[PDB]
Structure formats: C-alpha cells, structure tokens
Length: 282
Image 1 (spheres, one colour):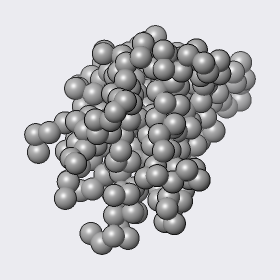
Image 2: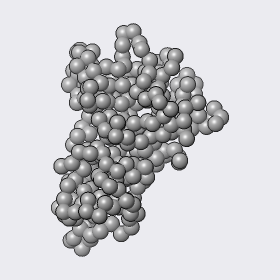
Image 3: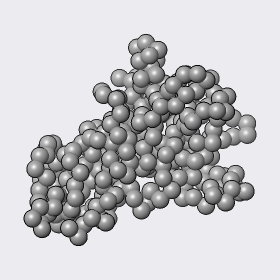
Image 4: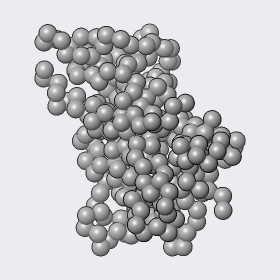
C-alpha cells in the first residue's frame, strides 16, 4: 500500500481522538465538581453553534463567548496574541489556530488555580480574531442550540484545548479533488463496502451531512443533565460516520464509518471528512 503516509491524517480516531459534532472527550474538576470539556486534537473547520437571533460569538450575558475583561483577553486578534506572548519563546511563534487554543487554555476557570479545565475557542480567519468560549456546551435541543456548519461559519474553526501544534501536518483541512476514499484490497484500492447515500447539491452540503453524522460525545433538563451537555455555569473517542465521498456529477454524498486506507482516483469524486473545511479543495 503506497497510501499509508498520505492517508494518516484521515485516521480521525488516531489524529483527533474525540467527538467532532459534539466534542466532550475529557472530564476535569473545577471547584470540586467535574465538568465535561472538549479534547479533540484537530481543529474543526467550519463548525459553529446555531442558537433566536443572537450569534454565538457574542459574549455571554452578565452568546457563548468570554465577556469583556480588563485587560481584554477575548476577542484577541492574531497580532495582539503574538505581542501578548512576547516573552514566551514556546508560544509566540505558533500558527494562529494552535496559538488561539493555547491562549484560551491560559484562562483560569472560575478562580480555580488547581484545575485542568481549559476553555475551548473559535478562531475567525476573516478578522484573524480568537474568541474564547465561556460556554463549552455545544448542543441543547434556557438556550436551545445545536452545532452546525453554517455558511456564516465557513471561516470559523472550533478549537479544543488539545489542538496539536503540528495539526497542519497530521489533521485534515482541504477536501481532495479527483479522489474517492477506499480500502486497500489485494493490491488495489476498492470501494468502501458499506456506505449510506444522501442527496447533496454541492460539496458544502455533503460536508454538512458528514458533520451531522460524525463522532459525537452527546447522543442527539436537570442540573445533572446540564453538566452532561457540557454546561458549567458517552465518549466517542473519535469513532463515527466521519468520512464522505461526494459525487459531483450525480450530487450524491456517500457516508461511512470505517477508516479509509487509500484513494480511488475517480474524476467524479471529492473526498471529505467531518473535520475538513466545508469549501476548500486541493
């Protein structure tokens, strides 16, 4: 199999290791109570939260984002983050996504200096702004809300505390043109044995469907049930329907849950994952 190195970044259980649609793959104590929190090692391109008319990057009421602080920690532009971490050799030069994750991970949770709980974040590529999320819950469907890849979220990236500094080398980002995921059998790349096929008028819509079916750490309202949804104020470990083959000609999205190990080079196909950018192709 000549595809082993190339295909490593699509091994989502290995490289990401947590939920995608809903990421709550770790638990951490804050002030004597254990909460769920995101722990995926890859950025999730295009993911946001749909709530109503307010947008989720609006600061929480005193939206999902950190409230106005003095000095301001969120939102913080890429330029401001690098300046802020000037004396930190090991942090100042990170790529913008990893830096955003580390910045969010330096916020103290509810005045507990002993806690391993670290807030997730969203990076906006358009404004180069890092938003720390005060609310780590991702679905409740009190706010009713759900994770999604909305067209308005196309430049957003959802970042857990664990996003690795080499994500560009080991995580999916762009979708693959002239490519259909397959399995390596008898020295040939053969079709995924079992796929579920749905209509999708373009790649974006297919990526959305794959995202809806992807690894999730909350299946789909007491205090218990609130903590179960990731509120603070069942672990997939990345197993799920994380991959799709999109036929651009027939407008069919073929979704499956077995890790692919090679590509079939078919000019009608684009290969996508739930982690992948919903539009970008290479």
